[PDB]
Image 1 (cartoon, rainbow, N blue to C red):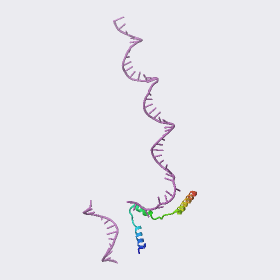
Image 2: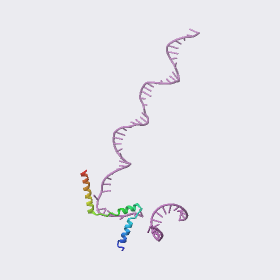
Image 3: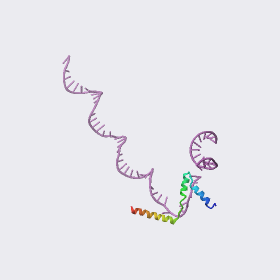
Image 4: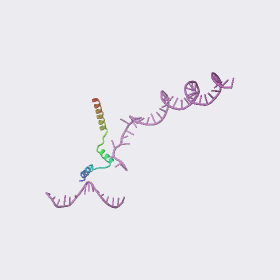
Length: 59
DNA sequence: GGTCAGAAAATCGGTTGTGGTCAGCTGCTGCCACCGGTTAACCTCCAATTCTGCTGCCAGCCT
């Protein structure tokens, strides 16, 4: 019953905590988003350039 | 053996004359102090006691 069940319960209980230090709170806040790779960075950059040209052209 | 023009003193003050003298910028010119931008192998989660009041918590009569 220790196969991520009680671990999940303690994970949600730790997620609903306070964590009264600001550095620890910022690290816990930034730990949620997952990492990337080269093709994902390429497609994000292409979307950035397309959106920037779209708003420039529309203005 | 006496009255009137001239000469000779500082004195208060205007001229004046130039002889520097100091500053007042004035470029200006070099420079130097300061602000802003840029760098493309990869490597992605911290360093004692004493007293009073308040709040959170669990059994437990009452509905």
